[PDB]
Length: 217
Length: 217
Image (cartoon, rainbow over all chains, first blue to last red; front, top):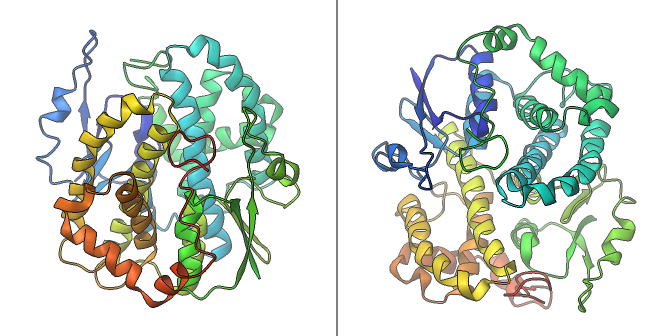
């Protein structure tokens, strides 16, 4: 079937794995392992990086027959397009493109902090800015069950990931924003998702690679 | 008409401006100025940041009637969808999604170097890495006039920007990659483009904000 290659990490493959699971996609996961010692060995990946036929070899990568895809957003969009989990009106396509990029911005702010040796000094700073961020997502979701209204689409898999992951980092962050909390419960409530989370193939942690100072493994 | 708000910089608005000119779009530019002294005064933007009705207030923004849009890729996509400067087949949509994100990564590698105070120490590393980056883009463009084949699309506006920008940073970088050189020439040769470049509203520099150690103004 399909092939999803990535580190044995949650990271950029989380929303991908959930969507594949949700759409009932048939796939195999090629999971790469990293070293621990001062040399975080990546030979397992680098050895076949150029032998899979990728135009821009990267992790994660999806291979579906003739289609070799890299870049997590392109991979999501690909599966999304195949199952109609995309925005329909231009109104919805706009929100989609905004959130797709907005979440990628949020995702990267956590990543920067969690890989920085000065994590301890920088963390409080992050936490003070976090509620401004969460407020805008809250404002945007409103009374809607999903981010583009009534129908679940690919952005919700992205949203879930970056929102839920912040809740592990700082457990109480979403408490002031009920609708965000409910979103997380509603997503996890979805039949295909809950069933997957109760399986042994889940993998919600480690969040980051072994080189991170937080959420590393 | 439309409104494009951004710093008085080339930056992330470059490819949007070009695409607006090319599509014959009518628009006004709300350009913001930054401070000089150790306090890079951004009050000009900050004062109205929350008064324009943006969901996720940010620069650049595009307001088109009821449509308020932030995130440069969402703005590009909005205009492109309007004038059909997008990919049609899934094959084209894939290359489009890959490229959008791949170009965004390239754009960010240069930005990080040029805003870094250790710029003079880091520049050598970037330069030795650049020739792997451009080769992948040559490989991908091949003998096609534009990145999705024969029809020009939005990714070409992104492409031109980051490729041409590297040529300003390092004049000889595209030397080994003729098709990339020709792409730049072909892009600049487009009627609406050349005309715009010969106008007083072009603004190809500064490349980065006043805080950049390179390309700053």
